Length: 451
Ligand SMILES: [Fe+3]
Image (cartoon, rainbow, N blue to C red; front, side):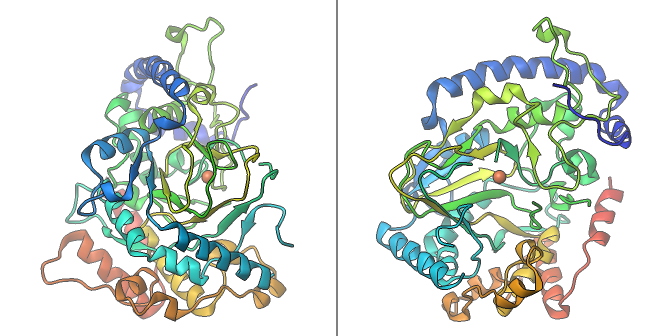
């Protein structure tokens, strides 16, 4: 009923985040927020899955989302793109994955997750021209203002190795949450600056797509994903109707994060039910749904105003791609009472950026050694480590130079004309590929001082 206390240091986190002079404004903003939430989340609940933005791969011209799709995607924080990959190609990839899993050990496994990272179908999927295209189009929804200095190149996609899911009917399920850290959004300096507009009482002007500060955020100050992903995503390897062992989302990005970020300050709902009776809590170290040191923020217990907004995604067809913003609440369906396997291949957007240089190095090292990337490799014992085989084949990259750069296998080109942070991050990556090591702290410390 009451969220637990964390250590009392978290009280000083609260007093760092909201300035005394802004307390009145923040309180007013929380009341405005709840009124908007009840209106908009009601509409979502009454519309259902068609609320999620959806478009056809052919609608993407010149590697840009059309204007109407863009506008809906920035509001709703998720998108389903249909017909990215032909069904026949999808079938071949699915069958090759299953073969690989059956020849490289129980099948089906208990959890519906298969720790295969570098198989040929994965490498081919990741680098299919239609897949590169949709990532290019997504990358144009994000931006930075300080182009001269911010160490990010949104024109470059890196590979973060991830696994596959093949969920049989009857396999039950991990509640509503955010990934990309449990407590960091509040605790880290640069991460919390992402949400400054909310902490100042102006949630309405929070821009989820501006990356100047997030570029330097530490998602792990201490279940953990080691890369900075702007978007989570996956490619559909099966046809499954809404609710059949798929994904559920809360398709309202700004309202979601205004509520989440302020919830530690307004965690006590009043007995009156009158929104005008909330009052700020700047004292208790309560950060509901958090477990410092873990990767997920849980929303299933102390975030009740969110629940009305949760919907299944639209019917999924083979060869559709589904994206959601790193800040979008989501969960998987509890049950799968559909007619066949619900299977996806996970692939997120991971820009070339200062907090992703370690990822670039891990990907290069794991693929070259045919082992798990670090986030999974670190959970294996000595025997498992010596046994695993990941299907990595340089030739699956089809000697495409751009693909090899995504995998950390080739230095980045820096054209005569290119400058600013884009040129600089490419150079820093190249230096790391030459030396084989990197230390992020210097860059982070400099960004935070510059504050
Ligand atoms: Fe998740």
